[PDB]
Length: 228
Ligand SMILES: [Cl-]
Image (cartoon, rainbow, N blue to C red; front, top):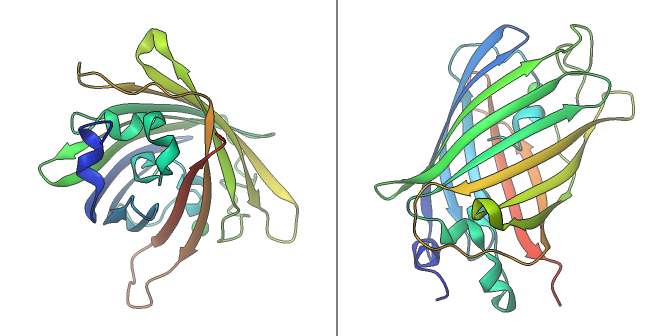
């Protein structure tokens, strides 16, 4: 295989996610577990709000709460930065602009801790309207399909990405969330720097019928594309 880190994703990998958030002073934490299967580009997570009631809609946290589980086609294997940075991992940082509303800033470390892939995140949100679509909880509990556009950032030995999420509004149009992303390796080992391509995402949100805590079950299907 074209990276040593790629070897770590040939089977099902257990996942842990931990997020600490503060949006307009409303603090919260989220803990999740699940598994990823990069051979099929699939991951499943159950995420719990461990502080009680989540003060923002679950859909607004989907992108923050594992691009190393993308399925890269065989002809694209030299473009998989994410797996090449494993097991030491990478930092993923974003600014997320909600149109006509506030923004999230996130910093995450995605790395192996033993045999488990862990995503540990800090999120800060500011400038939200208390009666906007986010703090007013006006978003549908569902998720559209999007492309994440990736380019190399050789100066940082990493990558950049951008994309636009469309969150359906209950009885309305959509709330846009414009994402800007950077990833840089944590380790010093060599990584794969890609040609321009994209990750095609499809996501499904659901609930565990036996779970009484505030939670989200998230299934993502992720496939790299955009190179002939
Ligand atoms: Cl929600």
